[PDB]
Image: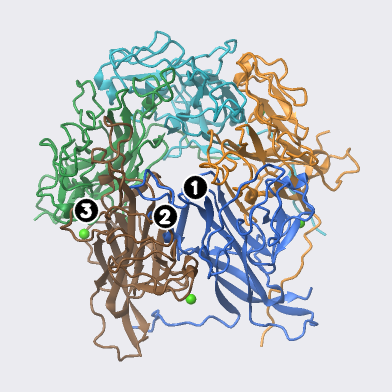
Chain colours: A green, B cyan, C orange, D blue, E brown
């Protein structure tokens, strides 16, 4: 016999330089307050009278969700040659409540006749998430520049037909939860150096939604130079939109259905040359 | 000539540190007892009168399957510095009876007219499995908070419109076979550190189902720290739901159709620092 | 100025320890004899009167194909400590006649109206192959236990509603070509240690079929322990089912359409501890 | 400072042992001659009267394309113990004219009504290519053995119901351009040792076609023994069929639409023991 | 304790040998001028009277976009045995405005009835981009040689039924923005040695569009010999076409919808044996 190693499993505290945060963001489909009957859905989609006259009603436009996570304070002040910053290195994220769509008894349009189950959520889907050290930078682009957007959303200022394409003046920050419509704003690829975003769109009138879920998948956030998002002011920005599709009522009115998203982000303390004047 | 090695194939009894279990879980679509005529299917889906009035009939709601496999006993003493635990390291799993869907003679809605084959199982599908060292932890979220769930399923306590999104109070453990509805409960990603789960959903009214089967594929259960699920009290929890779609009757009533799932899990004995 | 190697291409005969076999399996959709007008298709699918009364006509049920290939004999003496066995290490396989589906002039239902081409083969597809050193082990599972299967197919003995799920009593060996219905039998994932199988299913009433073909792809048959199927009694079992979809007649009666599959298997001699 | 390497870009001519060939093959959908109005398409698909009476009209059947590329001559006398042969080692291939399908103004069946765009090419698609050192070897298999094929195509000799499955007597070589129907002939997997073929099929009546194009992709032609097709008689065989779908006319008659394929093949000289 | 390395994050200059450019190209669907109401869309697609009489209206034909980016001047003149050239080595590219398609209120054809949402953009899609050191080389091929193309597009000269297949005389350079119709011209695979192009097509009358967006993906532009496009005259050519599908009006007339594309290209200075006579 001899002395040798055996690997024992035990609870390990990570080093002090590493932290994990967890958060969930509830959808902002238009009914955005938990007490509302249609929480998690938009109001009925009202369609344009004409191109000239297209006025979506209040709460009919799905908007991005965003949360700002306050991270542990790293610096006494900002006066040294270097400072400490949290660097986001990886994320596990999941759309929660996918199985809620496996429901054919909810009141709606019938698949066949009134003896059958009801048509489930389907049609256009849009799933995106972002993790950044500052607000996600947005580019404005719309289907129609003559749409009149309601007061409670942030739309493009002085919208003109050029906004049906890319006008570099149409830019915003995703700095408010449930205020920036998905149909008006998309991530700005000419910026976002300090954010990672990922998105998937499938269109079509009645297309079946497709979603996966697992707790086994991690997305590494390091860029091509091996650096993750660096959290300015010790703030982590989590952004998403998860439009599952539309639910159709028996009367054939339709409402958008959104689902919440969970994030679990690992961050590490980094020494960084002081970027603050 | 010289002495050399030649590899002879033989039945190897694995080292005592390793074990394998096999199990199958029958679906729990609502007719959950093998003596029932519609075993493997739900009863006819009854749809809501109104949002205010939505009362699914008993046995119309597909539920998760769960089995608890008792593993060989490891510790006759639970008071030492360390104890032994089974660590689940990999799994092979397969949906069984996929070929049973390849059937156009079963009575139902006709594809074209009364001379044609009948519409096979189609529509929404949902396939998930979990392997864990304790019950799968669940998060409640429903399409409508005003549904009244029957007393033979576990649903969200004190359900309110907030349950149409994520309310962190709506939590449960998958600790009962065939009692937790799929449409109410999903895996809770904020917990489940000691479980691995995998799921795939495709919706739509009439979507063709798509399924693969092979005995060549293994999923490794080790997490990012190289550790698999650790089986508390020497119990392995296997969970799943395999909704293949709906079958439509000639009358156009529809029933969910589920399929069984087979698991083959490899585990190894680990020395673990005692939690007590 | 120097002696050096140059690679010359020549016909190389493999080492004695390696052999290759080629085979093809014709489809067994119901018309299973090449003299039959509808060879390679089933007869018209007849649908159930009711759940209680579901009697598929003879030759309306697609069945698995199987071929047993005799390999060179290895052991004249079966009494030593070890014996030799053929180990299947890789397979190249192809569904043949895919291009025969690229045909819109064949009589049937019209795509648009009587001036258009005819609806091609489409709907439910099922493609599987297995390579093993013994018959593929099957599990019985049906869509309906009240179906009465005809006497020219092997069905589940003493069928009960429990056979709509997984009943471990409902087991068989794929040991007859064109007799085991696809809709009754699937590979048994709890056995088949000595076989590798691979299957793909897409359902739906009218789904477009999708198929690839190439002679550039090989599948390795080695399991997790680096061991391929071992051919008991020097017999190699090839199994498959390749249902391309259904053809629809102008009358709207429907028939299954199957395609042949080709196999090319490489095997190597192994020394194996003598079981008997 | 020190002597060191710096990489300068310049035109490099490959070694004498390596050569590249380019070719394109136009589709043979039935209208196979460039001066014909429907060049690149079949004639209207005429459907069977009955299973017994199924006679496709002339030029309604898409056929494989094949080109023989004559490579530089390698051997003076074929009586040496070894000879030289060209070995095809890689290919870049592309379906050309994919963008021609992005056309909703072409006359035809309307998507919604007479104010809308016209239904584009869709339905059954079939894309294959082969690169080999001899003709592609074909297996016959048909949907129906009682079809009567036209005189201008090569069909299965003495067709029988057995030809609805695999009959090993039904074999042919793809040695004539626009003569071997796709619906009769497929690559024979039991042969073709000296060829590489690749195919993709999607069926269905009205299925959307899906196609990719890029100049960044190369397929290596070496087999599991590290050897590519060897060009017998210094001849390279290029084969394909690229059926994009069917076009539907206002009258609802339908025609197959094919697209051309480009090939770029790299070959190297090899010393080969004389057959 | 000992002297050891610690990795500090800072803004790094990047060598003088490397440069990055960014650009966006707006779609050229037919309404190509920002002031036009239907900017970003074609005019209504008018269909042929017959095969012999097929005359698409002005501005109904989507065309390729192209931009020429002027890079930093590298050489005093072209008189030396070797010159410096920019070599494009990688690109990040994104279709901008994908989220704008997540809009069911825009006027149009109804999904179910006048109470429901409107049918979103769907049907034929075509997405391609190219990065090159000279104009993309094009091959002409049409669905019908008897179509009459408008004066304001570059069509195949002396079109004949042979142009329904590949005729080697039907060749062009993509050297004008919004002039070369997608349905006439495709990348010429027999040339384009000095360009990298990538394309995806999905046809069908009503097919749901599918698009991804992320800022985490880079395409390497080096060929099989390890060489990227070399920029002749210090000009980088960016080409694309991004047809999202068609929008259908209530009247059932249809228009093509295109979306802008962003490019971020990384280039390096190379010594090149002088190719200019
Ligand atoms: Ca920038
Ligand atoms: Ca947690
Ligand atoms: Ca077993
Ligand atoms: Ca052979
Ligand atoms: Ca060339």
Residue D107: which numbered mark, if any? 2
Residue placed at 70% from the left, 68% from the top? D134
Position of residue D254 in the picture relative to residue C187 (left or right): left
Q: Position of residue E4 (x, y in %)?
A: 30, 57
Rendered position, E151 above or below B23: below
Identify the secondary structure beneath mark 2: loop
Residue placed at 26% from the left, 28% from the top? A41
Q: Position of residue D229 (x, y in %)?
A: 66, 67
Position of residue D100 in the picture relative to residue A195 (left or right): right
Label 2 neighbourhood size at 10 Å, few (<14), some (14-19), many (20+)? many
Identify the secondary structure beneath mark 3: loop
Residue under label 1: D252
- For the question of whether residue C101 can be seen, the reply is yes
Judging depth in this view, the residue of E61 and E64 nearest the camera is: E61
Q: Quadrant of the N terminus of chain D?
A: bottom left
Q: Is there a contact, CB below 8 Å, between mark 3 and mark 1?
A: no
| Camera-nearest label, 3 or 1 | 1
Q: Position of residue A112 (x, y in %)?
A: 43, 24
The residues bearing labels 3 and 1 have C-alpha atoms spaced at a distance of 33 Å
Identify the secondary structure beneath mark 1: loop
Residue under label 3: E38
């Amino acid at each position: 016999s001899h002395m040798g190693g055996v690997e024992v499993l035990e609870v390990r505290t990570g080093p002090d330089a590493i932290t994990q945060i967890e958060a969930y963001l509830n959808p902002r489909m238009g009914n955005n307050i938990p007490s509302e009957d249609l929480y998690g859905y938009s109001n009925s989609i009202n369609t344009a009278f004409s191109k000239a006259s297209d006025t979506p009603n209040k709460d009919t436009l799905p908007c991005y969700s965003v949360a700002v996570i306050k991270l542990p304070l790293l610096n006494e002040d900002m006066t040294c040659d270097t400072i400490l910053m949290w660097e986001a290195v990886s994320v596990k994220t999941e759309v929660v409540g996918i199985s809620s769509l496996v429901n054919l008894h909810q009141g709606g349009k019938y698949i066949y006749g009134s003896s059958s189950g009801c048509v489930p959520v389907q049609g256009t889907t849009y799933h995106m998430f972002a993790v950044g050290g500052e607000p996600l930078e947005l580019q404005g682009l719309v289907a129609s520049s003559t749409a009149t957007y309601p007061d409670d959303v942030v739309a493009i200022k002085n919208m003109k037909p050029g906004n049906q394409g890319l006008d570099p003046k149409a830019k915003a920050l995703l700095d408010k939860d449930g205020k920036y419509p998905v149909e008006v704003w998309c991530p700005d690829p000419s910026k976002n150096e300090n954010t990672r975003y990922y998105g998937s769109f499938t269109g079509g009138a009645t297309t079946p939604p497709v979603m996966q879920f697992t707790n086994s998948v991690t997305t590494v956030l390091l860029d091509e130079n091996g650096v993750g998002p660096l959290c300015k002011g010790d703030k982590l920005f989590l952004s998403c939109a998860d439009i599952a599709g539309v639910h159709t009522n028996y009367s054939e009115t339709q409402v958008w259905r959104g689902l919440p998203r969970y994030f679990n982000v690992t961050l590490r303390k980094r020494i960084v040359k002081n970027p603050y004047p």
